[PDB]
Image (spheres, rainbow, N blue to C red):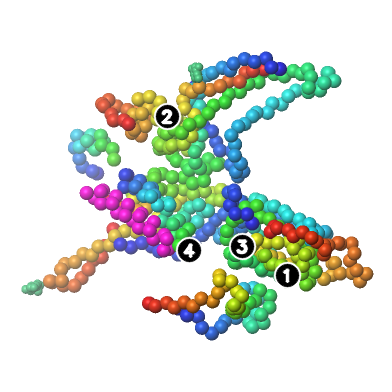
Amino acid sequence: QGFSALEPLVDLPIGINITRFQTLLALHRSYLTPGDSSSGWTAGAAAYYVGYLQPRTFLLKYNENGTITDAVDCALDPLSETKCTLKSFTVEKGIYQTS
Amino acid sequence: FELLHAPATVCGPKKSTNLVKNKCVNFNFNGLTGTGVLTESNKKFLPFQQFGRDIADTTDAVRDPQTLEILDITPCSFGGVSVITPGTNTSNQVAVLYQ
Amino acid sequence: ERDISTEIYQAGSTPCNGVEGFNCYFPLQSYGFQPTNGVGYQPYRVVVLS
Amino acid sequence: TRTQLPPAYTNSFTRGVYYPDKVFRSSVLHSTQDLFLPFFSNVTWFHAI
Amino acid sequence: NFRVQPTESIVRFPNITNLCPFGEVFNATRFASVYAWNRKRISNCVADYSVLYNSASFSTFKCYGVSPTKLNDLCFTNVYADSFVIRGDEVRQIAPGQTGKIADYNYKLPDDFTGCVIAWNSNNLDSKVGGNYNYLYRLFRKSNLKPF
Amino acid sequence: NTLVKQLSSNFGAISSVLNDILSRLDPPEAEVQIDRLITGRLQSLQTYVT
Amino acid sequence: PSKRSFIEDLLFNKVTLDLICAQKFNGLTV
Ligand SMILES: *[C@@H]1O[C@H](CO)[C@@H](O)[C@H](O)[C@H]1NC(C)=O
Ligand SMILES: *[C@@H]1O[C@H](CO)[C@@H](O)[C@H](O)[C@H]1NC(C)=O
Ligand SMILES: *[C@@H]1O[C@H](CO)[C@@H](O)[C@H](O)[C@H]1NC(C)=O
Ligand SMILES: *[C@@H]1O[C@H](CO)[C@@H](O)[C@H](O)[C@H]1NC(C)=O
Ligand SMILES: *[C@@H]1O[C@H](CO)[C@@H](O)[C@H](O)[C@H]1NC(C)=O
């Protein structure tokens, strides 16, 4: 449940169109059979997670050095909507206006 | 040549001039233009940061593309001018004031 | 503003000063007009009133 | 190796925030609009070997 | 009101230029055939034409559709280059959409062509008292080639 | 604060940077963008003063 | 040195006020 920030690494100027992708697994060849990698082998229990993205409006809090420490998603729930309405991570009593 | 099938990636390096400071001058930082005086800074940028901001349309720090140095921008001194008069009905003297 | 007389054009490094040598050019060209020339190359006549 | 099985789902909770620009700021709150991963999402998990 | 006028201008860039080569297509121990002139694409190279244009001892150089003095001021992508050797009399008959011998028909340029043409003398490399029979060319050709 | 933030809107022009417009277009074509920007900023100033 | 009464000091401390440089970017002044 912790919070972390993701840095920019590279921006390659390629310009080709991408619509599908596929991962590459480093297969281990248990070279005890004459069928090479087309035969009996063994490896670990690797797995991974893939998620997609959609356009959203986010509120970001910068600390005193310049690293993001907490973010608020605008379209989550009424508290999130109010906290996005006025720039603050804390709100006081009353009645507030939204979309 | 080919005509804009991809982002531009082939052209000259452009000539840089020696760095000067302590007197407010025009500047160009390959993406930043304007006029101001450049002073030594005390903030610490992240390694991948280029230029800082304080509020909308406010640039407060620029990273040197040569030596990775942080410089602070301060606009040239300016202000309105006013004239103090005892009225031409009596005499002709002025006490010009800078604000 | 009109340009009159002629000047020895200098596009190189060393000033030719009338030598007309390397990278040195004469800033003038002469048109070539013939009946067989195309319409796009035809010598039209233009007058401007201000 | 055609032994099939359906995938599994989890929550993203609050991960997936990245610096959108090269701009640096200090002790301020910034509002932006861009592509992100919505919190508490529907994420696939490929444990099939 | 008043303001203090600026007195100077400064422009900054990183020292690293990454000038990936250009000269390898201009100096070489071998040159491509006239009928099969080689074409090479160059990308992500920083142009350095300012010094190669003015001071490189090029007898013939001419740009169409652009001013050489500003060639360093604008950026392109994937610059294409060629290289071959011809005779002294064949340089004049090289032009965009220019007709000549059927050998000249083996190379063409677009009617609306923007670029530059380079041709420098070499009268001591390919010239031999016994003759130059090693390098062969086309003179009786039935087919004409397209621009570039 | 609102007033200053008003300076960061293009008002329907190509960009909100004054020098950028002059640095990428001919003056007879840049004048219309300059006029749009002037109109927008003037209206904002009027609202603030009122 | 700033001769004031005790309650005036409490009043001053209970009200809390660069922005001026941001205005100087645009000619605004105080
Ligand atoms: C910020 O930078 C200072 C040094 O400039 C460092 O001591 C500190 O650990 C950093 N992080 C925070 C949260 O202050
Ligand atoms: C100021 O002007 C009035 C009339 O214009 C005149 O009577 C008066 O003498 C003037 N003041 C002085 C000091 O002379
Ligand atoms: C995400 O959606 C799927 C249905 O598409 C649902 O089964 C799953 O429970 C959701 N995620 C979580 C963490 O509940
Ligand atoms: C720029 O100049 C400095 C000063 O000598 C040098 O150390 C550096 O390698 C040069 N290049 C870059 C990219 O900073
Ligand atoms: C090729 O190398 C020779 C050897 O000095 C040099 O004179 C010539 O300018 C080079 N051609 C280029 C760099 O295009």
In the displayed structure, would residue E82 be above or below residue F4? below
Residue in the picture at 42% in, 63% down: F27
The residue tagged 2 is A73
For marks 4 and 1 on the same chain, the one whose residue lies earlier in the sequence: 4
Residue in the picture at 38% in, 58% down: F32
* Magenta-colored span: F27-50
Q: Is residue A73 left or right of residue G30?
A: right
Q: Secondary structure at mark 3?
A: loop
CA distance for labels 3 and 4: 43 Å
Q: Secondary structure at mark 1?
A: loop
Q: Residue furthest right?
A: E130
CA distance for labels 4 and 1: 50 Å
Q: Is residue E4 left or right of residue E91?
A: left
Quarter occupied by the C terminus of chain C: bottom left
CA distance for labels 2 and 1: 69 Å
Q: Amino acid at mark 3?
A: Asp
Q: Amino acid at mark 4?
A: Glu
Label 4 vs label 2, nearer the camera: 2
Label 2 vs label 1, nearer the camera: 1
The residue tagged 3 is E112
The residue tagged 1 is E93
Residue B94 appears anywhere in the view:
yes
Locate ligand 2 by image quadrant.
bottom left
Q: Residue furthest bottom?
A: C5
Q: Circle 1: is it few (<14), some (14-19), or many (20+) Cα within 10 Å?
A: few
CA distance for labels 4 and 2: 47 Å
